[PDB]
Image (cartoon, rainbow, N blue to C red):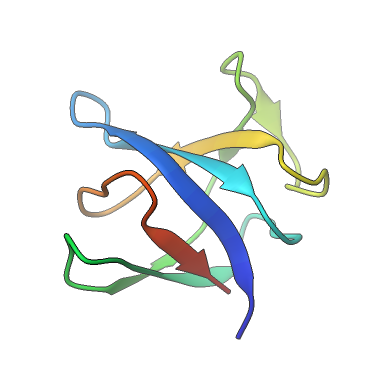
Length: 82
């Protein structure tokens, strides 16, 4: 179903994806990542942080930059569906 975020980047040192919100999502939500560079995989969202590295309870603000751990590398403009 819906487009929940656009991946902007991935930090291989920490395994943190930087995503820009497209629709509401929250910790515990199950998502799927896909894009030309990757094998798609499913992810449950754990802790989420804002652009300053402080925790967020939900990604409820359109176009907010949010950060969270992912189980595999991601590439710019990979998509996240909920």
